[PDB]
Image 1: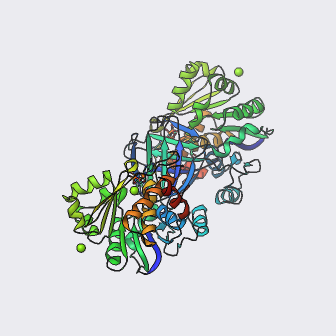
Image 2 (image 1 turned 90 degrees about the vertical axis):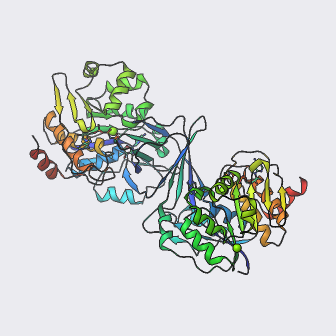
Image 3 (image 1 turned 60 degrees about the vertical axis):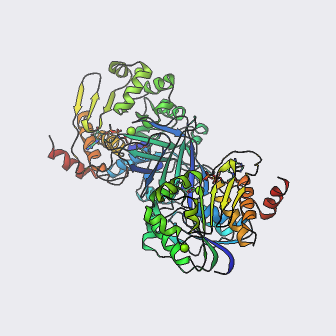
Length: 298
Length: 299
Ligand SMILES: Nc1ncnc2c1ncn2[C@@H]1O[C@H](COP(=O)(O)OP(=O)(O)NP(=O)(O)O)[C@@H](O)[C@H]1O
Ligand SMILES: Nc1ncnc2c1ncn2[C@@H]1O[C@H](COP(=O)(O)OP(=O)(O)NP(=O)(O)O)[C@@H](O)[C@H]1O
Ligand SMILES: Nc1ncnc2c1ncn2[C@@H]1O[C@H](CO)[C@@H](O)[C@H]1O
Ligand SMILES: Nc1ncnc2c1ncn2[C@@H]1O[C@H](CO)[C@@H](O)[C@H]1O
Ligand SMILES: [Mg+2]
Ligand SMILES: [Mg+2]
Ligand SMILES: [Mg+2]
Ligand SMILES: [Mg+2]
């Protein structure tokens, strides 16, 4: 691991938002004009944010036969994100979330696993990047990645919504091969209960535990110190989703650019502040200069 | 209208079809292992089943920028289905359905209208077919079709999943220009609540009212009589989705082939029994010989 470059491993996924009046009762149908498409998936959100910040990124994801000359493939190619490590299924569609949201803002999500079925027949390559960041995807494959990369590339891990799938054993084992561990508060609360861990137990295993708290900021724990990172004010909150992935993008981009962990947290906080300003996880990702400028005022 | 042919008016669509044990509640997520899109849309489904039964069909639908030279178009053309009257949008996508089936084969659907927004800009052509079958779609365009066709071509009407879009007044007016009216048990209930109609009110306006009841069969009401149509066993029920439209394809094909209303119902029922054996509304559409062979095994 040597090049100014981060590998993101895990979901590259299409999200489709369906705004409805009311969800259908049994034996009924609803009709809607259209669904809005968004480029998502935790790994691809992070990879695209890293690239936007001027750090080369590569993606390792299982995509499907619709990926494939369509919108998502060309959009990534256009941003110069390395997608040479993608696995292309002939049998299944690209993972995607179909998100149906009513007028009172209640939501029902159908996630298509689809091409992600292929991870269990795959094994990770040697990585040549400074950091291998492991996001939602297939936990067994993600553990293979962490075990292969650790002690060679820096490992970043953010189990996210996959958390419930990890056994205590398996979660322990991946954390033992992790350098940066990121979790939101609910995730951290969940994992700690599983593992019977307190903060000090994590720090016996990882170099930095980062717990994000949305609008209340974040905190970085190291063997040495606790670093409190403020929330950075957005222009106006539209879609609070994608704040997660983009904080990770900022943090890891800053780390590869050679800044200390405090400033990495600050850049993370400032990156996320741009992302909440629009619908979609990738639609308002900032440049490095814009991040540094926003941080400069607050 | 005099060609031994049927016009099908209404949606052509791509369908995702899912099996769940129970329908998800508000504020909940479900993972689907695997999904595939199927050729769908009520009007297209009927037009394909009709052709498969050996009756010429034509299709009128609004399709999207994902149609000209795509897999669906080439498939319909390969079928010798007249698609010359289709409207291709330049900016809207082909309509799409997400269909969920629970363990008791209840279904819910979500339907993206897309190119069907264009119906408000269009008017029907003259029809030269024996039957014009209106299968879902836009209420105002459908009323134009029925008013256009009525007393010239036989009008069959099956508002289907789009029924909620009909005001009482528009639904009433289309029925007054309808010869054959087809509804699900669910649709018939809602329709009758909306209209405040009993069976005989329908029969003052239409020649035949066909109410299907899934695995309980169906009933044909005319001014003269009530004809009970049994459910005809299928071999292993996989997907109920295509049952409704393939019943209309069988019923209307048999009608054009000159058989009486009872036999039309029996043919609809046996056609549907084949379609429910595979996922996708058009996957296991049967030939006329297969359907008849199955029918005579009954009775
Ligand atoms: N409303 C907000 N305004 C400004 N910055 C925010 C806001 N919400 C979050 N952030 C920043 O972005 C980071 C990520 O928030 P986070 O706690 O990970 O959200 P989350 O619980 O993961 N929800 P999601 O982003 O949809 O997965 C935080 O550490 C905040 O600094
Ligand atoms: N399980 C079955 N096996 C054999 N034939 C069936 C079965 N279910 C339905 N049919 C036939 O198909 C006809 C139409 O059923 P139908 O009343 O349209 O069900 P449905 O609720 O509309 N399906 P859907 O609208 O997609 O949820 C019936 O009258 C039956 O003859
Ligand atoms: N249940 C789930 N499991 C894994 N990934 C998901 C799930 N729901 C949504 N995602 C994807 O992950 C990203 C954020 O977690 C979104 O862009 C979305 O596509
Ligand atoms: N709400 C709806 N409006 C119109 N057509 C629908 C709806 N839901 C499902 N469909 C379609 O009806 C068919 C079954 O009759 C499917 O092929 C599907 O495309
Ligand atoms: Mg260790
Ligand atoms: Mg997250
Ligand atoms: Mg129907
Ligand atoms: Mg009359």
